[PDB]
Image (cartoon, coloured by chain):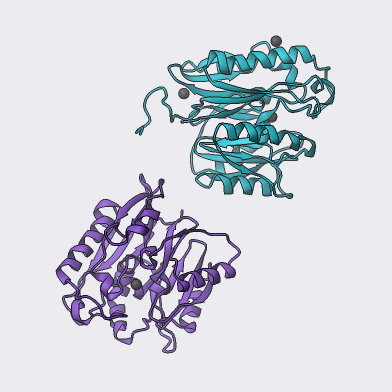
Chain colours: A cyan, B purple
């Protein structure tokens, strides 16, 4: 196997994926999806086009094998597959979402991950809730946001499932997920917002950790949600929000001269709090 | 982190071990030269291969059992309990082990109560709590003194069948992982231990009770390390250990010292110094 830390990537590198699971959005998303704040009307056709372009980046441009689950009109939030599963190595934790009406989304995700021959562990404890959006996996450990959607028991079950990794919790403000203001932008590199709320969470995370991470600080918390991938024969890749959406944050990502930067629009789904990480579950099948 | 260690205390075996060491059953003749080579290989794993600083105490021909240092001290974090062994004739071994642990700058607590006995072989430390076997060598008062010494950790007792120590059929094989034998006795003791603790331990069950005695270490730049008995000695138990794909497995022969009931944990005291 691999030794040392050199090179631009290999089949066991941090952020390597081979597969992605996504799910189409239903027409009912526009009116019936849950959302943290009143806001502008969702253009569902535009949201569909943006989702289609995002899937095209993962599958066509970057070469992942993409499993596209069909929309369910009775599950308006079903596009946000990250909340229903957390995958680490060959094990998939099927979560118990904090919003009870999203718990129906679990079935089809579990089916897809079984077909990919992952080891399946299910949250069934009636006292446990966990949204995948509250989970930051750094490659070395997990941080789990304690929010209105994820509680202490859910974090405990995650820690029981991925026993080989440290798990620590951090309080998250109401209406937010942990990854509403952070994500990994590269090996040992955490993208983080500049708000007092985001900085308070980062401090709690870094004081719980036995490691020192580097930071990529962006002026817009929402734009700290990005997707880092290590892609064969391409190397470090970063999907990030567009200059048209967050020009001041795009200026920061543009400094990453050793990344392949891919701007990806999410402006319509953001209206129902959908960001980049929310729309896929990434899997490394070795 | 569970299983961290920086130092080990061992003691050379005397020529007198062959005929004069205590043994629970008549059996084969001990090949003392072979036992010495096996002991040297064991010490080589701890010190040279794994990088522990090993304190090697000299043999005493008048103390035929002195190689079995585990029985005379229990070390938890910065505190050493110097035990009062159940076999009176082994109580002379205490002096030199106390001296060695003093030089390692440990806090020393001595079992001196004339009503108390405890062998270190009867003590299983899981990382979360202690289980203490009540055997022919370890009694209630000894276990109470251990609980008073390690006040940060829960302690519970479990009865052990005559002629055994608790770790004659169990030991820690990793974080939250108890290696355990399959005999009536072993499974009865395991059931009592689990009934006494809320914590759910994982089990590594082996068909040979003796092969459940192993040494787990967490070594920097290596990770999980496990010293276990060889396939030549216990092939059906080695097959169970070979399944631990995230452990660095180190087979270690102890066939000669097993004739005088000496297993893997018996021959060292492990210490984590910061
Ligand atoms: Cl667009
Ligand atoms: Cl990088
Ligand atoms: Zn989300
Ligand atoms: Zn012993």
Looking at the image, which residue is at 71% across and 23% down?
A70
Q: Is residue B96 left or right of residue A197?
A: left
Q: Is residue A18 above or below residue B119?
A: above
Residue A209 seen in the figure: yes
Q: Where, quadrant-wise, is the N terminus of chain A in this rendering? A: top left
Q: Is residue A89 left or right of residue B49?
A: right
Residue A108, quarter of the rendered image: top right
Residue A215, quarter of the rendered image: top right
A77, B95: nearer the viewer: A77
Looking at the image, which residue is at 38% across and 55% down?
B217
Residue A107, quarter of the rendered image: top right
Q: How many numbered circles are shown?
A: 0
- The location of residue B121, given as percent across then percent down, is 38, 73
Q: Is residue A95 above or below residue B264?
A: above
Residue A178 seen in the figure: no
Looking at the image, which residue is at 56% across and 13% down?
A60
- The location of residue A257, given as percent across then percent down, is 48, 15
Q: Is residue A270 above or below residue B161?
A: above
Looking at the image, which residue is at 60% across and 18% down?
A240
Write down which quadrant ligand 1 falls in.
Answer: top right
């Amino acid at each position: 196997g691999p030794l040392g830390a050199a090179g631009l990537g290999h089949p066991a590198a941090f952020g390597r994926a081979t597969h992605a699971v996504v799910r189409a959005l239903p027409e009912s998303l526009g009116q019936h999806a849950l959302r943290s704040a009143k806001g502008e009307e969702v253009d569902v056709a535009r949201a569909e086009r943006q989702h289609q372009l995002y899937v095209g980046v993962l599958g066509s441009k970057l070469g992942l094998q993409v499993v596209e689950l069909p929309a369910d009109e009775s599950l308006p939030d079903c596009v946000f597959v990250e909340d229903v599963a957390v995958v680490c190595e060959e094990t998939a934790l099927i979560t118990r979402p904090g919003a009870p009406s999203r718990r129906k989304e679990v079935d089809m995700m579990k089916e897809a991950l079984e077909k990919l021959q992952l080891n399946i562990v299910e949250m069934k404890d009636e006292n446990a809730t966990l949204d995948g959006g509250d989970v930051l996996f750094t490659g070395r450990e997990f941080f789990v946001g304690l929010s209105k959607r994820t509680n202490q028991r859910g974090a405990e079950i995650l820690a029981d499932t991925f026993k080989d990794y440290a798990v620590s919790t951090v309080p998250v403000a109401d209406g937010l997920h942990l990854k509403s203001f952070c994500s990994m932008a590269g090996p040992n590199l955490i993208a983080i917002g500049s708000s007092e709320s985001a900085q308070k969470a980062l401090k709690i995370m870094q004081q719980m950790s036995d490691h020192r991470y580097d930071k990529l600080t962006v002026p817009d918390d929402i734009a700290a949600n990005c997707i880092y991938l290590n892609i064969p024969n391409k190397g470090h890749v970063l999907l990030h929000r567009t200059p048209e959406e967050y020009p001041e944050s795009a200026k920061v990502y543009e400094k990453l001269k050793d990344h392949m930067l891919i701007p990806v629009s999410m402006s319509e789904l953001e209206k129902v709090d959908g960001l980049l990480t929310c729309c896929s579950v990434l899997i490394n099948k070795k």
